[PDB]
Image 1 (cartoon, rainbow, N blue to C red):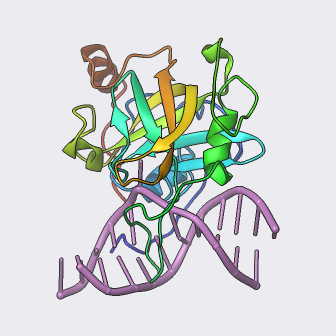
Image 2: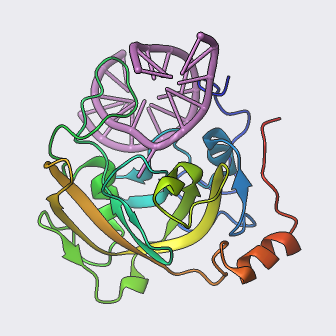
Length: 209
DNA sequence: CACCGGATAGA
DNA sequence: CTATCCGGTGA
C-alpha cells in the first residue's frame, strides 16, 4: 500500500522554491518510492514529472518512462512537457490526445533556459547561466534508457535547459521538447567515479519507515 | 488494469 | 476551492 500514502516529514532545510541542490543530499542518493523523494526536498511533487512555478522556473524533474517522446542520453537528454492528455475517470496517466501548451510547468521549465520566454521556443547562448534543474532518474525509465537505475529513484544532479521547442510527438499531437545538459561538479552516478562515491558516502536505497 | 490519496500551484 | 498528475496498487 504505497499507492495512497502521503509524506511523514518535509524539507525545511531549504524552501519549496529553492533552485539548485538540496544541501547535503548528494548525487547518487536513492529512494525506493516517489514520496521519499518528495520528503528529501529533491522533487516535491508526488506524481508529476516537473516541479515548477510558471512565473519563476522549474526546480526539478523526474525521468520515469512515462512519456514516449523523452530521449535519455545520460549527460544530456530531451525531456517532454506535461499535459496533452485526457485524464477523465480520476486517472494520473494516459497517452497523448491533444496538443501540449507552453503553460504551467511546461512554461516553468522554459523559464530556466537563459533566454526570454518565447512561444515558438528559444535557445540559450550561455546555457550554463540559466537556472539549475535537479534531475531524478527512476527505474521505469529503464525500458528504454540504459542510464536508469534498476530499482526506485536516483538523484543524478543539476542539469540546465539548453533549448526548448514544440513539435509533433509520436502520437501526432504537439509536445514541448526540452534539451537538458548536465552541469554538476560531481560524477554521474552510473559512472565508476560516481559508484565509488556512492559507496564512499554510504548511500543506500532508502526504503519507507 | 481501473482508479485511489495527497501535494502543489494558481485562481 | 479546483485542476493537474513521468505513481503504484490488489488482483
